[PDB]
Length: 19
Image (cartoon, rainbow, N blue to C red; front, side):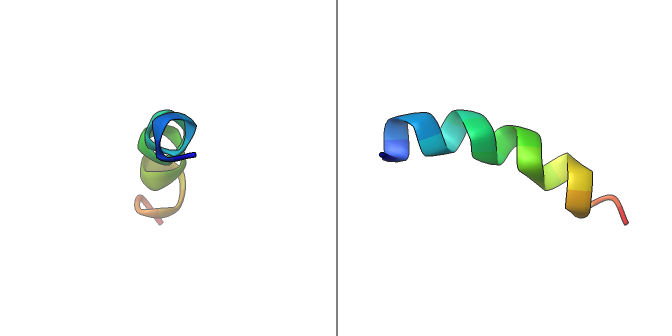
């Protein structure tokens, strides 16, 4: 589900990619 994944991915990245 790349469609939904992109939306969630955009949110998950700044959460872990910030620490």
